[PDB]
Length: 193
Ligand SMILES: *[C@H]1O[C@H](CO)[C@@H](O[C@@H]2O[C@H](CO)[C@@H](O)[C@H](O)[C@H]2NC(C)=O)[C@H](O)[C@H]1NC(C)=O
Ligand SMILES: *[C@@H]1O[C@H](CO)[C@@H](O)[C@H](O)[C@H]1NC(C)=O
Image 1 (cartoon, rainbow, N blue to C red):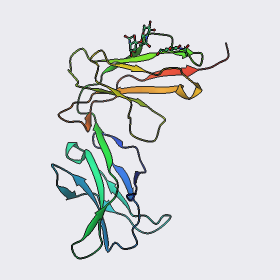
Image 2 (image 1 turned 45 degrees about the vertical axis):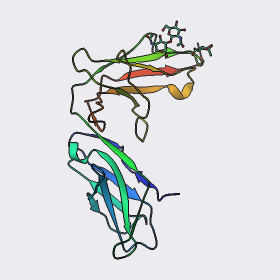
Image 3 (image 1 turned 120 degrees about the vertical axis):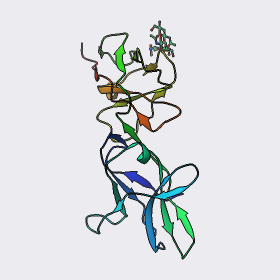
Image 4 (image 1 turned 180 degrees about the vertical axis):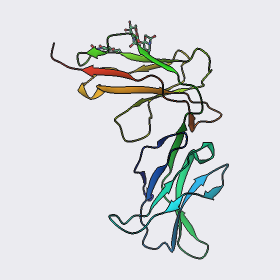
């Protein structure tokens, strides 16, 4: 098990936003610094916070841009020149490409168990892949699709599927750089009808 590396704010940060990262404390570390990976090379980044309301080291990265998007790890210097790292965290920056369009082939309100797929298009920008995000959620959108027609299925829906959804740009060359959110699309599952 590797030291955890959570993100207090969403891992999805708008163009010039700012995010707060937290690493797992390691009693034997003389120094702990947030590192960002770039071409198999660890680079110092972000800023350390002060001791209060929490123990595990917290950092903060502001003025988000392409350069700050990507994989992150925590570097624990457990000696003059001996280190160990936390698990990996990914941060994506949004607002680098025009917004795509999200829609559905059904009715936005539906009985549980029903099936529905959301489609995310882009009649201009040849996005390599697409990612669907559920607004409320505190994390990183993992539900993606490479299909050009862009199909996001949700199999048998349950009351938990309800909520507002948005879709993003996304390019293979530059994976951690997404477009501006697409139009939002609300769904509501209810067994009452
Ligand atoms: C994307 O989702 C699945 C493919 O993974 C397709 O599902 C079929 O959808 C048609 C009409 O929408 C239904 O008649 C079939 O019963 C579905 N079968 C499956 C695979 O579950 C879906 O069509 C695709 N998106 C669309 C509508 O183009
Ligand atoms: C939803 O679609 C699946 C195919 O992926 C089908 O097997 C299922 O029966 C449909 N809804 C239900 C649970 O009846």
